[PDB]
Amino acid sequence: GVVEEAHNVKVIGSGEATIVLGHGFGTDQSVWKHLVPHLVDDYRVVLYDNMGAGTTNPDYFDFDRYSNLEGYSFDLIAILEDLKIESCIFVGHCVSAMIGVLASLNRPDLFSKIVMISASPRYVNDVDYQGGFEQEDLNQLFEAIRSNYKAWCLGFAPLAVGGDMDSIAVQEFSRTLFNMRPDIALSVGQTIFQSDMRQILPFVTVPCHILQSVKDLAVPVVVSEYLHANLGCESVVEVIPSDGHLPQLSSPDSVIPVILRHIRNDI
């Protein structure tokens, strides 16, 4: 149907046992390329793209619908309902971790477990919370996006990915970033970076696994500990000895075994 086409939905592999993978800002379902091979023999795997990703039709990007994360959560629930999925393990990268959380508040019955990669409920610092950014840092980022999008993409991609600046992963992310329509990239970047999910964390009821790189430009390690302390569900943290905000793409040898362990084993 239109929902499946519009979000480039793929369903692979075998099982009532179902894993659904949601990607982060600036990438698409291809971020999961090193994980999916190790899931398909044991799970039905669902991949999809967030509306506003470069692989999606910009005519479908509704600036009102996506002015908060709830719009994306409604898309996720829609996909699950369209595919007749009654329960899934949801793996959410970056903003998808919070999209999944929000979807789970509305429909906890649809999720057995959330596995978060590179998640944060809040990026902006305040006097009692370290998110990684001052508002002035974000203001400059948004102005660079507006002023020259390609320049911004080429500078941002090595910082977000980490590691060597000439890596295949840096090149890949630079390409997916620049694939976004500039106005959509700006709008979405503002929505994510200005989001605040902290206050709803006590209401979460689905168990969460909180994974991140020890070095992540957008996610100080204390954020993992904040999620663990404030989520209302059972949770566990594992900080990985990896660099980068898309570590399942750029450092798979160290990262994929950790993700698999948290998918395959319950708290």
Image (cartoon, rainbow, N blue to C red):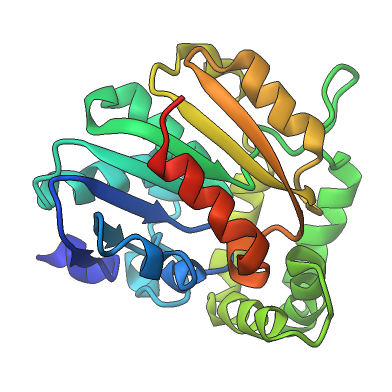
Q: Position of residue 173 (x, y in %)?
A: 63, 76
Q: Where is residue 135 in the image (x, y as percent from the top left)?
A: 85, 41
What residue appears at the point 20 percent right and 71 percent down from the top-left corner? 5
The quadrant holding residue 155 is: bottom right
The quadrant holding residue 251 is: bottom right
Q: Where is residue 37 in the image (x, y as percent from the top left)?
A: 38, 70
What residue appears at the point 40 percent right and 60 percent down from the top-left corner? 50
Q: Which of 218 and 55 is in front in this view?
A: 218
Q: Is residue 86 above or below residue 176?
A: above
**Left-right relation of 60 to 251:** left
**Left-right relation of 15 to 262:** left
What residue appears at the point 9 percent right and 65 percent down from the top-left corner? 1
Q: Is residue 2 above or below residue 134?
A: below
What residue appears at the point 64 percent right and 47 percent down from the top-left corner? 118
Q: In this view, does 259 lie above or below 124?
A: below
Q: In this view, does 148 lie above or below 193?
A: below
Q: Position of residue 40 (x, y in %)?
A: 28, 64
- The answer to whether residue 96 of the structure is visible from this angle is no
Q: Nearer the viewer, residue 202 or 177?
A: 202
**Left-right relation of 88 to 161:** left
- The answer to whether residue 162 of the structure is visible from this angle is yes
**Left-right relation of 49 to 4:** right
